[PDB]
Amino acid sequence: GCLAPTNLEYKLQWYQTPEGTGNNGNIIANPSLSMLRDQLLYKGNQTTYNLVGDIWMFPNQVWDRFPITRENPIWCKKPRADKHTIMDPFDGSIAMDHP
Amino acid sequence: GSGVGISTGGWVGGSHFSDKYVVTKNTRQFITTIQNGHLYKTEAIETTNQSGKSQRCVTTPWTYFNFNQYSCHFSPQDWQRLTNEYKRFRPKAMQVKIYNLQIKQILSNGADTTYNNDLTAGVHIFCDGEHAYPNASHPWDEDVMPDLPYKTWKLFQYGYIPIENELADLDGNAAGGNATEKALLYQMPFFLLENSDHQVLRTGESTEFTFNFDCEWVNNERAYIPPGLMFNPKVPTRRVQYIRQNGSTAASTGRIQPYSKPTSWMTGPGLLSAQRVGPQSSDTAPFMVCTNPEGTHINTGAAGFGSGFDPPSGCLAPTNLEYKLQWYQTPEGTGNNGNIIANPSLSMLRDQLLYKGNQTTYNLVGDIWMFPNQVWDRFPITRENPIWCKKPRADKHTIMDPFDGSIAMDHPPGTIFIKMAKIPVPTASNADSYLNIYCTGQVSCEIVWEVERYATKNWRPERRHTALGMSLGGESNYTPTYHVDPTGAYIQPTSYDQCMPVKTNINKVL
Amino acid sequence: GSGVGISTGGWVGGSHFSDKYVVTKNTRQFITTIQNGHLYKTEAIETTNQSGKSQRCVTTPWTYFNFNQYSCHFSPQDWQRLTNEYKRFRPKAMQVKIYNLQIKQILSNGADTTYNNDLTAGVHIFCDGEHAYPNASHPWDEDVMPDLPYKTWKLFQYGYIPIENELADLDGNAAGGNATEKALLYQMPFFLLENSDHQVLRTGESTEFTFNFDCEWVNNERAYIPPGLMFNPKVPTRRVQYIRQNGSTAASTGRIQPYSKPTSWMTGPGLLSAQRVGPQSSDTAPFMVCTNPEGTHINTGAAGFGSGFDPPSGCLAPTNLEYKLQWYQTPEGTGNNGNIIANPSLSMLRDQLLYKGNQTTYNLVGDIWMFPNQVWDRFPITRENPIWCKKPRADKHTIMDPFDGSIAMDHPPGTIFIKMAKIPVPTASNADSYLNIYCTGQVSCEIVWEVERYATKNWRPERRHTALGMSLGGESNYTPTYHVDPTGAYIQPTSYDQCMPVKTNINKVL
Amino acid sequence: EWVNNERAYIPPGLMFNPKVPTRRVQYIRQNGSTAASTGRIQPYSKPTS
Amino acid sequence: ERRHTALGMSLGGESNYTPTYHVDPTGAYIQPTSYDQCMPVKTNINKVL
Amino acid sequence: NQYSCHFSPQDWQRLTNEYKRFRPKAMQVKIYNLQIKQILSNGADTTYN
Amino acid sequence: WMTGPGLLSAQRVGPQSSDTAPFMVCTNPEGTHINTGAAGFGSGFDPPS
Amino acid sequence: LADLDGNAAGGNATEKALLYQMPFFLLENSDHQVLRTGESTEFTFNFDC
Amino acid sequence: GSGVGISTGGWVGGSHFS
């Protein structure tokens, strides 16, 4: 979420009304042109730079949020558990206690 | 009375110390210029190399007051008394007044360059305060209010970056030539400060603004022990151990020693793995954070075009000079004479480390992210650090916790913009003409700091900022750090013991 | 307080959007000059060719503020938000303020050309508002308030045409020499703005005027079907047909098909038959409307001396480039680089046609006049079109309906005239002398627009003004349409998709 | 919580004014060869928190 | 600022025409093609950050 | 739970163009006008009464 | 939803009798000590993962 | 008006611009009454004609 | 009234923007 997908495997594909059945029906969920989204982090060694694949929560990260389209779910169920985290679903849906 | 010949306000200065506040008043003398042609343009900034890079930087006729540093509000005396006598402080409110304006006309024949005031000329003065326009101030910028009074403070032009220049490019057509390159240009925000309603002032007028601050405290205290030492080493603990077989060396099960008990607490986040890159002249490095809507660009070349994250490994042992702050100092040098290294503060909630044991001995973990139970405290702001930083508008974020030490506020005190009203001149067609004038006046920034006093049960004497850590000298010599040379030079503080960082003093029991 | 050294008013700007209004505030910086000798004269305008033509044009020392365009009141942002979010709008009221005047004296030795203010000098400021004097403003004229703030706006001289020059002539005596030629000259209205009572302002003063508007709405909606498609094609209609024998091909009587039912509604008026004429340089063409009290002149030569009717075939298919609007744009070019074609808006109450069937197939009717049941809608004003036009005082007229798209009002907001008081100088006899000064100040035009929001039962998404129809670029490139060049140039909007015409968006069900 | 329809148009790292100088210096490791030097951050490309 | 135009809609409905949000000659509803149809939030307006 | 069920394409367009942020306050659902039919199948008729 | 945080990579070290291990968290104001020897003098984080 | 029909024929661009905005009206968008046998309705009207 | 032969509620639809 909030990283450059760098491949099709990291993306949303709706599909659409149930047929297809693919790949005719699916849609790729292209970037929204923010600029709080997508991004990247490069780690410089002595010479040039290399993309850091996995970057976890770190202070000062500010990523905005997935740009929900008209077909996205409105909310999602937020599990009952002691602790959790920012939450921030990557599907774009709102996580509510008691939807 | 009012009008020309009547001073609109008086000078004001000095600080006052009370149990619950320090109200620090400062008045400075400022100057403006025509600041381009009164017209905005835009500028690709000339880059030294030019290997490649640029920035779009629409520039404005406006110029702005930047109040953000501690050194401008506090004298070295007052900073000393603040960091020694109080555990924590935050600003409640700030009040600024522009008054006693003199608008002079610049008359240059090539020799005289006379200056005679023009009444009826005026200056535009606009305090954003909604943060509707792109923020002018940025932490660590020069353009801050100068340290000393009696030094004229020259205002700096206001400009801002529209869409990042590396993204589009184009440049290439049919090269390409890409379509998403242009989609970023077609929407490029373009901000005029004339869109907003704002005041025009002739000589007789003054203005005032104020502000209010919700900001978090900045804490002057030191830990004296890591959080892992809370335990009483006299009493036994039950936690046992085990171990893997490893070896040979058949594994055994045994109790934790009374000393060296377990710790639930963890090392504050920071990233040590990265390294600076190459020529300088840009960016430089490490941990460049950039956006790459796909593909842009990608390409990719050259690698790493984007904003760098300068002081990673906040609350970690720096382990090298590259991870540190270096101020410099007043703009020359130019290095390395002027820079200062920002040495450790001796907490003990700062610095730290994390070692990862394999079967045999231990190895430093370079990059450690946010993890529960991490408690790192915060950067020990000195007198030259910025007070606040602008906190971006975005949905989610994180602890924040800037590593520069500055407070991250939603709505920092709004930047105050000033330009001088264009005075047009009759001319043949085109010929932007106008008239060469400059404004001069007095800004008085009165900020109230909510402050609170320490009380300790420690028997032993605590550390304080002595002023015997000051150093000569002033070219030739003598002239201690906060003082003035035989020439008017102010002999900026050498090293890190001068400028008196917070968190070095008092104590916290944790 | 009051007097020199006290700004009389502040800058003001920006627009505000509410359900029922958009109040758009704009402040500009203006400049005046001595504008002839303070004396009127009259001028036969030098004509390029000079095949023949002229105009009488009594010129005045006065100069005037022309507020009539949409682009001056609305930013591209605000025009976009207006045309996207609202079906119709009209101005309720306008308020103008002249304030912060600087009257400078021009001192020229041939080199210095110094400028030093003269207090006690003054400017005359007169708002007609009764339309007792000939109107200064005319649609599509430059002299309108400039698009951008921060651009100085140079005022343009006020002049008006007394009796048409072609009518008299004379010129010929005994040639002749005609008697009715002179009868038109003997009564030639001659207007002095000093006849009227008006204000004189020194630096300390400001003025304000306001206004009120009775004007009709301008509607942003699109038809999506001609009025002839109202019918339900599923249900049968009774209207029968017949036909003539023609042929051979013996005529038969039969029912109208369910599709293609009759229509009571008719094509809006317009005239396609005329053509442009020749050299340019005057008039040019088509449909010159002129007066010819008999015989004058008649003669006749050369043919067609009179005012041309530029955009005939309002609400008709243009069928050629000659029938269209071409803005240009900021004054250079000079063509054809600057001009823009004013493409169709895709209503469907616009454009259209009428075909006249003879026995075999159909033929376009070139000129179609007012006829009952014609319903044509109206020209889709863009951001650069004039807001209003002056509606002549006359007994009768017609629908009106200007083809330029501008609103025709009885009593448009009165033109505001400004000259600088003649400052005389001692001299030997004759020697009109006086003194060279110029005025500079700030006009703030605050106009309130009555506005109303659309609601549609359409399921499907409607068209909007994207801003992705904007185009590069700024010499070299990038710098999208509403934005500023690396040089201060503003990169005027290319084509017709930029500048965002009304009636392209939303829908009307008819 | 709200769902926000807005776009950033710049990364958060571009907040700075590129016209004004910044003090933050740099250093670098020796690397190389290529003896390391200490120098100021350029006015463009300022640090980002 | 950018807006959702509805000129980014696409044909078509088998055979053709029948733009995205609309109905085929058969009762089919011709679901929106790609991502420009269905109009995601955060593409429009701006935030100054 | 979807946005497409509550908003028409027209209304989604007008929502994402004209407003910076939105959240639902309240939802109200009504089940009414119930018809309970019996399915009678002999293998051919499959009548419904 | 995602897995709660924890660290499985580390291993206990050697003789016991101190500290023992894994994930020793310690402070090292530079250089102290650094040295470095022996490695890992500081408080251990006992139940990671 | 559109036609298209022809592609590359053409194939014209303004042909499609008329299709992309094609109003499509559902009477279910509106709020309206449902009646069983027991109910009746009444409306009236008024005429300025 | 109530019972079979009386519609319990009417259709409703459309959105409103404020």
Image (spheres, coloured by chain):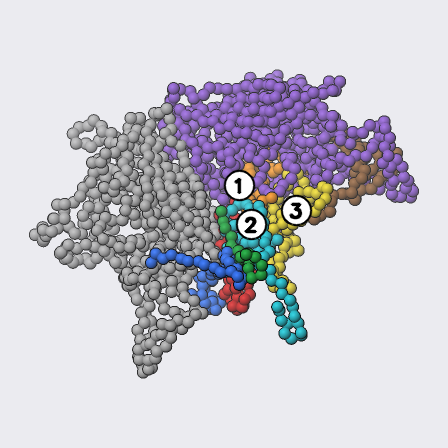
Chain colours: A yellow, B purple, D orange, E red, F cyan, G brown, H blue, I green
Res D45 → quadrant = top right
**For mark 1, what is the residue?**
E48
Q: Are marks 2 and 1 in contact (CB under 8 Å)?
A: no
As drawn, H15 above or below B120: below
Rendered image: mark on residue B379: none
Q: What's the CA distance linking mark 2 and mark 1? A: 17 Å
> In what element is the residue under mark 1?
loop
- Identify the chain of the residue marked 3, using the numbered disc in the image: A
Q: Is residue B368 visible?
A: no
Quarter of the image with the C terminus of chain F in it: bottom right
Closest to the camera, between mark 2 and mark 3, is 3
Q: Which residue is mark 3?
A: A98
Q: CA distance from mark 1 to mark 3?
A: 34 Å
- According to the image, label 2 marks what residue? E41
- The front one of B505 and B157 is B505
Between B416 and B438, the residue placed more toward the observer is B416
